[PDB]
Image (cartoon, coloured by chain):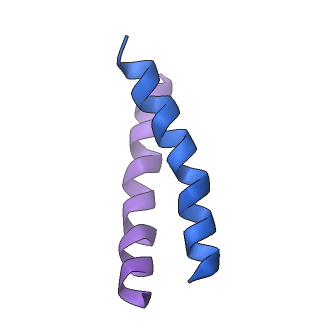
Chain colours: A purple, B blue
Amino acid sequence: TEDNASRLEEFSKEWKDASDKWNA
Amino acid sequence: TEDNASRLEEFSKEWKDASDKWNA
């Protein structure tokens, strides 16, 4: 569970970067 | 674990919105 949570906390940065890129 | 699951259930809506936007 904690490993999966760490994976998602890592992936959220990538998703935020993608959303910021696509907002422009 | 339950807080992380709630976070992912919230984020899935945003990902679905992004996929729907990019399908057009």
Q: Depth check: A10 or B20 in front?
A: B20
Q: Quadrant of residue B22?
A: top left
Residue at 41% of width from left, 33% of height from top? A21
**B19 is higher (above) or lower (below) than A5:** above
Question: In terms of depth relative to the viewer, which is nearer, A13 or A7?
Answer: A7
Residue visible at 46% across and 31% down? B18
Of all residues, the one furthest to the bottom in this rendering is A2
Residue at position x 47%, y 22% from top? A24
Counting from the top left corner in percent of width and height, residue A8 is at: 41, 68
Q: Residue at x 39, y 40 (%)?
A: A18
User: How many numbered circles does the render carry?
Assistant: 0
Give the left or right position of residue B14, taking residue A2 as reference: right
Residue B19 image point, x, y percent: 40, 30
Q: Is residue B23 above or below residue B5?
A: above
- Which quarter of the picture shows residue A10? bottom left
Front residue of B5 and A16 = B5
Percent across and percent down for residue A16 are: 47, 48
Give the quadrant of the N terminus of chain A: bottom left
